[PDB]
Length: 272
Image (tube, rainbow, N blue to C red):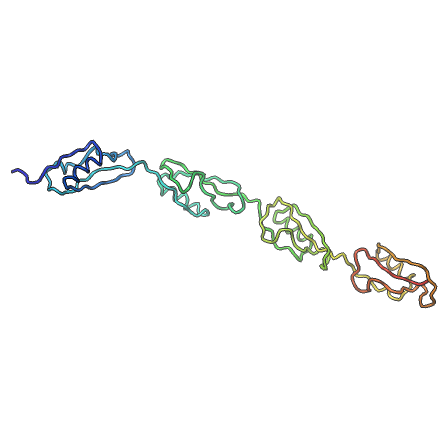
């Protein structure tokens, strides 16, 4: 006959709080089901389940249908070199709306994704499109080790790398003239190909002078002139000192057999 089960008053059409409050007061329990987006029944009670409207035992669980606000996704982080995973991630994020832009960038960002133009840690809508920019187009390269090679070879190596602008600075060195001492920037330094690279060149500024010891100046003179000597000649006073000194070279300031300065300055003396 009459059910000892109790029919539970419904209060749908108001709010979740009021509905739950009524049931909770009576000792009933509820189950709340959330669904993302408000295109489906809002979090406020518009409808309920007739379980409560039926005679049930006091202390049952009534299901309430709730929806949560608009769906947005926070953008997952991905390795910049892994564009495939990046696009995958936007796709797995719902929207899957992405653009790929290439921009000439600083050498370190070239070759990989730099990020997204909109904030990549923040939320984007499922209808929102994210433009992703990848660094492309380098005009920078790292200069190789170039020391011990000739200037001609050095400039050639630099030109091969695309460094068309070079300048060579020659400084005196024990190292022979022509050997590249090194470069202004060290090896491995990434620089623009359109930059002017400085090749520092060893300048020996020395050439070996042949023996002229104990000979006559009548021999010394044509020999020096013949070898293309052009410097400063020290001819002092003519001194009659005897046979040992007659037109004989007394000493040669730069020792025979070694390298003499680029000037070639020879100090020699003869008597008369």
